[PDB]
Length: 50
Length: 171
Image 1 (cartoon, each protein chain N blue to C red):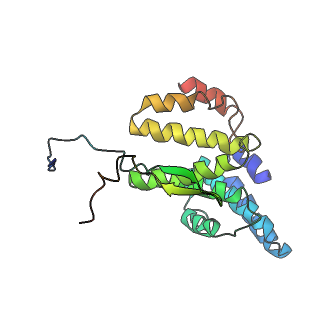
Image 2: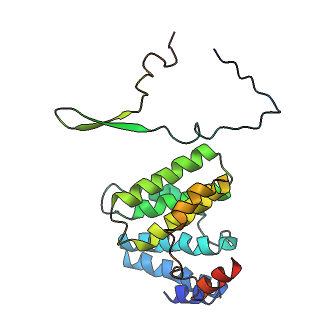
Image 3: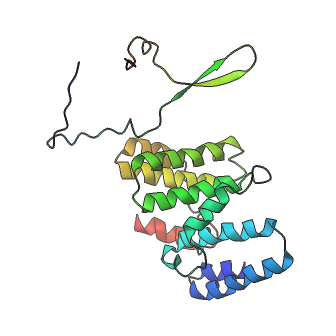
């Protein structure tokens, strides 16, 4: 587990968070639907609810 | 249009009095569709000359709230216009970068959804904002790609005719 506590000497701000997250195009039998993007390995790496 | 001609010669104040009387005549006709044409012309004039935002009888924020919920049909290009004006105000207001990107996303998605070739004016304005937006972030690599699409000497209506020559001279 990484612990990146906020430090004044670290000005390396992040912009990927500000930019909106991507989406995915998956088509089922009925129609083409749009779902939020998840990394192929994010299901077992996602932030756990528990 | 005479007000537009007045704005082309940088008269500015003389155009305001001429435009003001345009609103009164529109009410007498009692037709809704022409007011949107009037309202769109409002902020286009303020966008070129932001120093006159106080002189108008309607603040710029009032228009954005009206056009966003204007209708769901028979607008086509109104919403494409509506969201870009919010983006300029948000950029000027130095709002949070999360909101500016989201607002610009709204304008980029609606412009490219329909034909961008026919609406050459807004497509150029998209490029001008996006180059300016990303240049402000400090990423010239992204700005360069969009810069090759900004058209030169094309300029826009109601803003002089030698503005393109002057702008090229500044650089």
